[PDB]
Image (cartoon, rainbow over all chains, first blue to last red; front, side, top):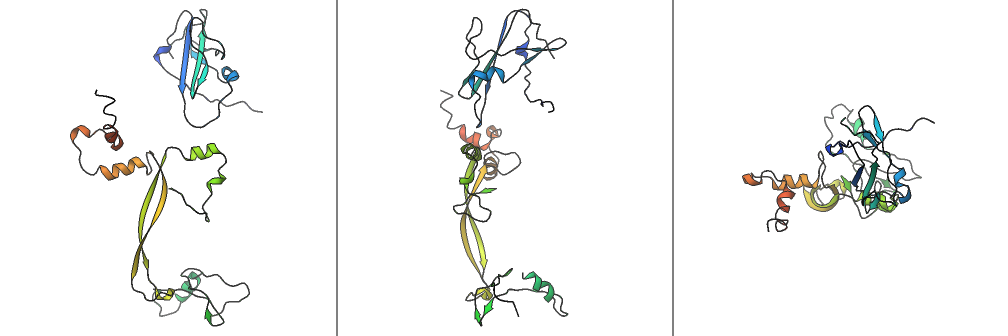
Length: 99
Length: 50
Length: 114
């Protein structure tokens, strides 16, 4: 009946300075070991993404498995043991600034 | 267990040190086994004597 | 070390009783085998039904060990290679290689340098 604990990863890099326009981001994770695979049609519901702002964090939904990014080919999916996660930000979303 | 005999042989005046010690089982005057330096198993129906 | 055996014993657990196939796979991951040839001297004792005493018999046997490939603070295959081969000073140009790197540089030669 208590709260859930926090568990995750943080990635710090300079490619993430994104201030204006329509932006498309793609993460690719290359994994190993022996573990079960999450069913496809719920991938976009397993993770939550936060991006750095001026005064707050910015949340960004993950694109579901059956559709492509606008004017491009990037897509959320499994590729053997590689995991692809794709995020779109619209032109009215705040800038992504250094932490 | 042989140590129970080791610690009592070491209590006799005049005994300096024990260089070797082992035990063996006899029934009806005949040796039943080869023996062992550290422990010996007894038969169900019999009481040990010297 | 983790020892392997052909027969059951007091502290010898059967691999058949692993929880699942993935448990077996994670058990056999990133590990090597070594076969060790071990010598010992058995003491003769006339009190133990030997024909005589005051002597020793030399005898040897084999043991199987499952060794990790690379662990920073424990025995691993890389550590054994380092101990065995890196006994003498190597030429200056090789000083920065590990033993398996100094071995692989010679088979991966032609993929590069062509």
